[PDB]
Length: 95
Length: 95
Image (tube, rainbow over all chains, first blue to last red; front, side):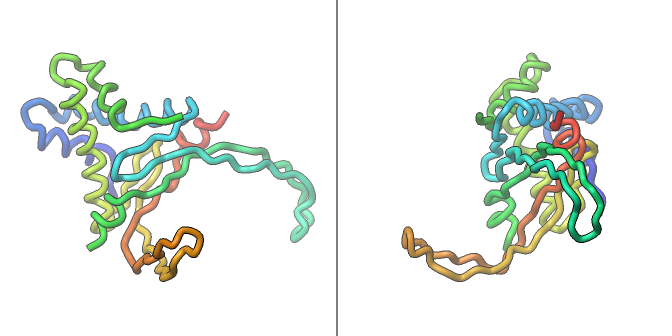
């Protein structure tokens, strides 16, 4: 199955029937995924109670001659977000 | 640094002040995450354009007891999920 955020933004318009319309609930859903991001560059662990918590990790930068292939390397460091699953995705999801 | 679902609730309530209120907007904010939890149940490839992607995983079983606290380790063979990061939460989180 494919699933994209318009599928999420449609749903909440369809169930909060008289306050969210699909045309506005697209923006409402935008600010979900925007603000996670603005938090995660600010220094923060974004906790979503029952669901899990997203925090940052850093990869080390690597330099040298790769000793399998002999190719020289100049790979820099970088940060990324990662995730730790909670009960909604454990015992609520598992039957 | 730390961030809750309560501040995701305040965020949209700032934008649409007369139709969304920070306690009301908690439930709107929760039902996004409830509809992604529902999707990873059947096994849908939840791929949020720019944010990243959500798919299944199987938990690996572990039967044991931590001697250093006295707690049982009692992981079954269970359904869970996992995130794979996309461009907003790696490449442009990263500077």
